[PDB]
C-alpha cells in the first residue's frame, strides 16, 4: 500500500496543492474521503488534534495542518531550496500565500455576495509581491525561489488557479505570473493530474461558491 | 549583532522571536518604527507584503514572523532532532498561529463586544496543547522531543498573553501551567522577561490586552 494517506472532505480546498505535489513528484497516496455526514456524527472530529482536516499519515506519523504537511513533503522529497537561505525564502513565500489564502477562504465562507467586488478591486496589490519575487529570480523564467521547484510553487500555483476562477483574467496585469502558471501547468505529470476526473470533478470549496 | 529586528514599539509578533534570541544568548539590534514614520509611506512600500516585522541576518532580509522563527530554528538547531520531530514542531507552531490570529482579531475588531464569548471558548482552544504535552514524556520537557524548539517560544508567548487577557485561564491545565513555570525560569529567559525592553512595551498596537 502507498506510505501516504490523505483524509479530507471531497473538495480541493486545503489539499489541492499537496495532491499536485505528490502527483508531480510521481508518488502514490490513498485518499480516505470523509463526507459531511460522517463529520457531523462527531467521532472523527473529536479524534483530530485541532478538530479539523486535513489529516495526513506517512507510515505511522500522523499530521494535521495543511502547511505542516507541505513542509514535511518538502523536506522528505527534497523540495525545500538547496541551502538554508533558499529554505528561508521558500518559507517567506508560503507564508504570503497562506495570508492571501486566509482572506480568500474568509470571503467564500463569510462575505461572498457583499465582498466579492471589494476583494477583487484589492487583488492586484495582493498579487504584486509574487510578481516582484519572480522578477528578482532569474527574470521570472524558472520557479519562485532558486532554480528547482519547491513546495511553495505548488501552493502558489493553486492559489493563482483559484483566483483565476474567482476573478477571470486577474493575472492579465501580471506577465511573469501569467507565464509562470502556464509553464508549471504544462509539467507532464501535473498537466495529466490537472485534467483528470479526480481533480476536475471535485469542487474548489465546501459550500460550492467559487 | 548579526541581527536586526524592525518593528513597531510593541511586543506583538516579535515577542516570541525576541524571547528566542534572548534565551539563546544571541545579540541583536532593534530598529524601532513609530507610527509616524510608518504612515509617511517610504518603508512600507519597500516592505515585500507591506508589513513588519522585517529582519536582517547579515545580507539576508526576511519578512513574515513565522519565517523568521523557522530561520532561527534551522540555523540555531531549534527544529527537532530529525525529520519526524521537525514535522511535529511545525504542527504545533501552525496551531499556535491559528489561535494567535483569532486573538489578534479579538483585539483589533471585536474587543468590547466579543471578549466574553472568546474566553468561554478558550479552554477548547488550549486543550490540544495540554494533550500534546501529555504525549511527550508526560509533559515534563518541551512541546516536542527533549530539546527546546522555536515552537516552544511561540507557544510560551501565546500562553503568557492569554494569562493577561483571561487571568487564571491555565488553572485547569496542569501540564500547561507547569510548562509556563519551567520555561519562564530558564536563566537567560527569566532575565529578559523582567527587563524594561520587554516589560515596558505594550502587547498590542491599540493598547488593548
Ligand atoms: N489550519 C488548518 C485549517 C484547516 C481547516 O480549515 N479545515 C476545515 C476544512 S478546509 C475548508 C473549510 C474552511 C472553513 C470552513 C469550512 C471548510 C470546509 C467544510 C467542509 C468541507 C470542506 C471545507 C473546506 O472548504 C475543517 O476542517 N472544517 C471542519 C470543522 O472545522 O469542523 C490547515 O491549514 O490544515
Ligand atoms: N503574516 C505577517 C503579519 C504581519 C502583520 O500583521 N504586521 C502588522 C503589525 S503586527 C500587529 C498588528 C496586527 C493587526 C493590525 C495592526 C497591527 C499593528 C499596528 C501597529 C503597531 C503594531 C501592530 C501589531 O499589533 C503591520 O505591519 N501592520 C501595519 C500596516 O500593515 O500598515 C507576519 O506574521 O509577520
Image: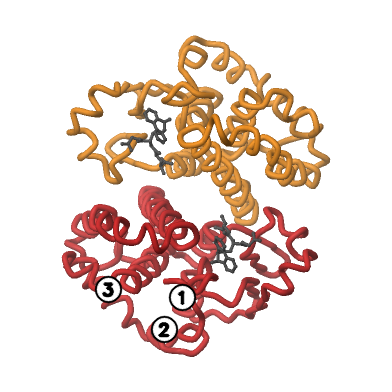
Chain colours: A orange, B red
Q: Nearer the viewer, mark 2 or mark 3?
A: 3
First-in-chain label (2 vs 1): 1
Q: Alpha-carbon distance for marks 2 and 3?
A: 18 Å
Res B19 label? 1
SS of the residue under disc 1: helix
Res A113 label? none
Residue that label 3 marks:
B167
* Residue drawn at point x = 54 percent, y = 24 percent: A210
Q: Are marks 2 and 1 in contact (CB under 8 Å)?
A: yes
Q: Chain of mark 2?
A: B
Instruction: Name above or below for residue A204 compared with residue A107.
Output: above
**Left or right: B85 in relation to A126:** left
* Residue drawn at point x = 17 percent, y = 33 percent: A43
Image quadrant containing the N terminus of chain B:
bottom right
Residue that label 2 marks:
B193
Percent from the top left, x then y, of residue B63? 63, 59
Task: Evaluate whether label 2 is on the same chain as label 3.
Answer: yes
**Left or right: A98 in relation to B187:** right
Q: Is residue A58 visible?
A: no
Task: Evaluate whether label 2 is on the same chain as label 1.
Answer: yes
Amino acid at each position: 500500500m502507498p506510505p501516504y494517506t490523505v483524509v479530507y472532505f471531497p473538495v480541493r480546498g486545503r489539499c489541492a496543492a499537496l495532491r499536485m505535489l505528490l502527483a508531480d513528484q510521481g508518488q502514490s497516496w490513498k485518499e480516505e474521503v470523509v463526507t459531511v455526514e460522517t463529520w457531523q456524527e462527531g467521532s472523527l472530529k473529536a479524534s483530530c488534534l485541532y478538530g479539523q482536516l486535513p489529516k495526513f499519515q506517512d507510515g505511522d506519523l500522523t499530521l494535521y495542518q495543511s502547511n505542516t504537511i507541505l513542509r514535511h513533503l518538502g523536506r522528505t522529497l527534497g523540495l525545500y531550496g538547496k541551502d538554508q537561505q533558499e529554505a528561508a525564502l521558500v518559507d517567506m513565500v508560503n507564508d504570503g500565500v497562506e495570508d492571501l489564502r486566509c482572506k480568500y477562504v474568509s470571503l467564500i465562507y463569510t462575505n461572498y455576495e457583499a465582498g466579492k467586488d471589494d476583494y477583487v478591486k484589492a487583488l492586484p496589490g495582493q498579487l504584486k509581491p509574487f510578481e516582484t519575487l519572480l522578477s528578482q529570480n532569474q527574470g521570472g523564467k524558472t520557479f519562485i525561489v532558486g532554480d528547482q521547484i519547491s513546495f511553495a510553487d505548488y501552493n502558489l500555483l493553486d492559489l493563482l488557479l483559484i483566483h483565476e476562477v474567482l476573478a477571470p483574467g486577474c493575472l492579465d496585469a501580471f506577465p511573469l505570473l501569467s507565464a509562470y502558471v502556464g509553464r508549471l501547468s504544462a509539467r507532464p505529470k501535473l498537466k495529466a493530474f490537472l485534467a483528470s476526473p479526480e481533480y476536475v470533478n471535485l469542487p474548489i470549496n465546501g459550500n460550492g461558491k467559487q
